[PDB]
Image: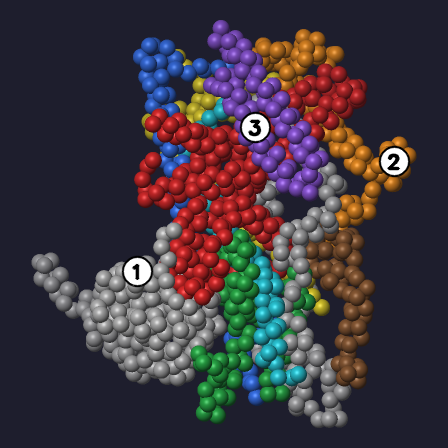
Chain colours: A cyan, B purple, D red, E brown, G orange, H green, I blue, J yellow
Amino acid sequence: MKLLPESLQQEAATAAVVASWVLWHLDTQLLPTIMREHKLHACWAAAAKRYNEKLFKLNPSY
Amino acid sequence: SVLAASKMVGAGCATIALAGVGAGLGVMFGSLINGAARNPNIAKQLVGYALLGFALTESIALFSLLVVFLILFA
Amino acid sequence: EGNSVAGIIKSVNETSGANLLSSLKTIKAQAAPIYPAAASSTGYSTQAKIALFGALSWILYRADGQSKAHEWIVDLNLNVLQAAWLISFSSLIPFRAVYFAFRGMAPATASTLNGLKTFSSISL
Amino acid sequence: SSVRDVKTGSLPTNFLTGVYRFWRSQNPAEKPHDPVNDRLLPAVVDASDKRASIGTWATTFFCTIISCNLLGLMPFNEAPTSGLGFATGLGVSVWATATILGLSKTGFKFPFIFVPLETISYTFRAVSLGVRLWVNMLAGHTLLHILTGMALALPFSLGFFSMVPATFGVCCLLSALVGLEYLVAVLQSGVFSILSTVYVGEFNHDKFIGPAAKIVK
Amino acid sequence: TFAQRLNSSPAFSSFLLKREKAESEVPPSELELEAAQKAAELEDPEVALRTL
Amino acid sequence: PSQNLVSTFANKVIVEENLVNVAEIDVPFWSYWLSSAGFTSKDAFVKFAEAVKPKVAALSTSDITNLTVAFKRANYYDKDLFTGIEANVSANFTKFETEQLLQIVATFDAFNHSSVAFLDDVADSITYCNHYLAPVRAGADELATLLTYYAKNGHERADLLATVARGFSEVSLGKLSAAQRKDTVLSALKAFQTFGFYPESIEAVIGAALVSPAEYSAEELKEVEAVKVAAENALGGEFVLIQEG
Amino acid sequence: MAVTSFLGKAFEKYFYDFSAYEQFGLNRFLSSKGQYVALRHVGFVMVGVNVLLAANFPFNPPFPTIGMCPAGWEGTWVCQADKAKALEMYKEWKKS
Amino acid sequence: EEEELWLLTLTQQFKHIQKHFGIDLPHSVVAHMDPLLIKKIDWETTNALEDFDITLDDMGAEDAKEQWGAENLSHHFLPLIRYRRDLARKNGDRYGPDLVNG
Amino acid sequence: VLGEVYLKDILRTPPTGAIPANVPHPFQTSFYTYATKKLIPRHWYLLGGFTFTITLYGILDGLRDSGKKKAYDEAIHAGKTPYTAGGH
Amino acid sequence: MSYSAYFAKAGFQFPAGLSALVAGIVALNVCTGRPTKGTKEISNAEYNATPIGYLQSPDQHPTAFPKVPGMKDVHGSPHHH
Ligand SMILES: [Zn+2]
């Protein structure tokens, strides 16, 4: 049993590579998709009242 | 091999700090039970504090164990 | 691919009065969204076969290195102790409740879409 | 150059939405004194520009650390986190990220014997953040290996199918230990990211460039 | 209903959710069931014209 | 004998004609990067304009704003080309982003080129087709260029004014230098007085002239005070400065 | 004709339908289903460690014995604590 | 039936989204049906404002959250706005909402 | 009437012909846009932290190699073996 | 109907930039600068001089399922000082 590895810098660079890939994949592939779903639902839920009142005012059918 | 003998003796004397950290951790978890009994409406908040508290408390155990490793396998 | 409602309008205006009630179902089926039917079941993907063969090669390589190791038998028994928990998680975890809990984690799936109402966008 | 199609409402999307909203909620934005409207909206957008992305960073660290921590519990696998350089490199990385943010706030200027004592107390966060998670992963694997040898010894020196109750008891103890290792894997990933959020939120505070001139009524 | 649409979703075709039903987690209301019946009745457009 | 050879190779192959003849494949790309590197010669851009002129109407939005910025830097105005660019912008205005439209409107404001349909499509694209915080990321000189463009052409669009008034604040005006801030404040206040539109964010313009009135002359201060009194009457109160606290 | 389709359907039928808690009628011996899951977990561990030890044996264990042998190797080449001595004793035991 | 295409396409698009959204709707069908909403959403992720509705919740800004949602779906009224503006242009008048004093 | 040309790229119906391709984010398209728009302006603190930890661990590897080479040098100068051979 | 068959059409797919992740981990594990663990960079004359079994140290070839802990598969260099 050894505490230290063969190279501390190699393991540190492995951690940096893995975490930087998780950062790029999060910011680039995951967070656009997440925010497309979330901001569609949130924009509709935040604008339902104003949207329906504006469309009710525009609608000449009544 | 008097150095390795003292390594075994020193690691066995080194892990005494786990007693104090276990007594403190049990005090903190018993207070978590108490604080959930006082006000359960915020209980899922309190457990979070407990975990965070356990977190920092656990670190005092690991700085013990690290010294044990620094005694045993350095 | 044009507007489907514009196709509904053109197809309804293009029919005669005698043909309208007969052709309403076909005008409905023409401007209805494509839900693509199930294709023929094929082989596994290139990436799926790469994943399975790479997982098997990693498992074999790690089991070989665990055999070569100094405390080899406790390595091969740690594998049994971990596979036991992977077995017991398939039996313990309430996967329907876990699915709906994760659905509650995101606000997009926690509630229904509250958006356009019918009375605002009606056209008499 | 063509991206893949995603089903809306998938379980990984919902899980990562909840995780991101959690680590984003750890450092909430401050309410301004003025009401938020179009006069205050560039001040709000610049406040969000000056705030560091601790939600993205904490989600990054949570996902990578829980992935390595759970890799430690798959068969034929050890955690990368149980390595010293990996876990303590992540810890020194979070401490240096917080320090680089706090230095850049102070104009890239480095910071009455209270200042070296607080310097050592702050500098020990670099040791503690990585050594905690690394020590927990190393201790759990080491404890399992020592415990497994004792369990193996019981049926090696008492017959394969000749000692059922003691072998059953020690395998119950080993199985409860592996369940504890699952709990410790999840907990230490969450602890690393919570302490990451508090360490960077010590320096996340910035000036709100609000309105300097207004119509009073 | 929303539960029937969840049962027809891909997520309930996956292996860990083959035998599960979404009604057992949250059942549909009486309004939701009668509105699913009413919408199935009004899926014929000629019936909708006559009804209106 | 290599020096006579390199003198023969240096005056016949590496010339401006082969430079503008290799720049025919992707001409908004090449005109953009050659104009940024500093190559602003007239005859090359005369060649470049008839290079793009067929294929303008099917260009991308990034290539349109690249070509328009390049011809802004070369200062060469081709009426049929900018009619083609204006028709491209008016054709697919929903695809254009606000920063691209601000660069395009800056080029169309350097010359006096405008249609009614182009102005309505740019205002519709900035207002409706783009994010409402896109003027916040703009920089107040670009927005003041757009405001003076719409004021010069007399096109009144109150929704576009309410959109690009959002970009004027303490932040975006504080990003500018002092002369550029004075020019931007004068342009924005003149355009807002032309339109008769005094939003709640005009005061961040007015304050940017009144926190530092040392750079402003007396007639410019009279103009700023005229817009200040007009905004006081429109917004419904009196204009104070806020101190540090 | 396909192999992975039958493998998926067969593992589904084994995972979901095949239940030895009701097929063997273990509801009389055990209280609940979760107790059966815990005992099947620990029984999986016991059978696995016995198959590994039973698989390849007789060998000098790298894990610490508590001073107990397998009752057939008092001091041959399996219970030896020194490893080089156990190696040469294994060699003179393998020559036989 | 002067403007029934615009109202009926709004009804049909929202009915399909609301029918399929959290269940099985692909992202491609959403970006086909509402491309400008996806564009305005991508602007927030691009310009590091992907937590802007969380920021408006942290600041307690319910009016600004309503304005944010209404300004993201503001393009749904753009076909009607352009049609009525072209009608008023052919009649020779000005469009009412375009003017500051309208 | 309000034609289809007013609805051209603003507002579309659900697809009847085929399901289109997914519209990429600008970050999914190019790494240059991600790097210049979000990775460097927002995450340069994290990148500087990774750079600092790799630099610092290279320094620690240098110190460990210097101490190890020093021990090896005095071991071969003392005439003894620096390493234990062992038993195979 | 539903879009279930549309998603069943697409097979298993990797995370989008996983090839860059595996390339970075492999490039960290093979481009180290130092030689392979256990091995020593010797001269070309010494490499061409020695046979295969003498060049292999016994510490680098452990026995697969060793009956005794410390069994090595090869016995290298009986000719030594
Ligand atoms: Zn292990």
Task: Tell which residue pokes out farthest to the top in this image.
Answer: B2
* Residue position marked by numbered label 3 in the rendering: B57
Q: Residues within 10 Å of mark 2 (few under 14, many from 20)?
A: some
Q: What residue is shown at x 55% (from left), y 82% (from top)? A: I4
Give the image location of residue F183, x and y in percent. Answer: 27, 68
Q: What residue is shown at x 52% (from left), y 18% (from top)? A: B68
Q: What residue is shown at x 53% (from left), y 53% (from top)? A: H58
* Residue position marked by numbered label 2 in the rendering: G26
Give the image location of residue C50, x and y in percent. Answer: 57, 49
Q: Residues within 10 Å of mark 1 (few under 14, many from 20)?
A: few
Q: How far apart in space, not on screen, are marks 1 and 3 (Cα)?
A: 54 Å
Q: Does the rendering let one see residue D74? A: no
Q: Amino acid at mark 2?
A: Leu
Q: Nearer the viewer, residue E12 or D34?
A: D34
Q: Does the rendering let one see residue B18? A: yes
Q: Are marks 1 and 3 on the same chain?
A: no
Q: Residues within 10 Å of mark 3 (few under 14, many from 20)?
A: some
Mark 2 chain: G
Q: How far apart in space, not on screen, are marks 1 and 2 (Cα)?
A: 86 Å
Q: Amino acid at mark 1?
A: Val
The circle on residue F211 is 1
Mark 1 chain: F
Q: Amino acid at mark 3?
A: Thr
Q: Are marks 1 and 2 on the same chain?
A: no
Q: Secondary structure at mark 3?
A: helix
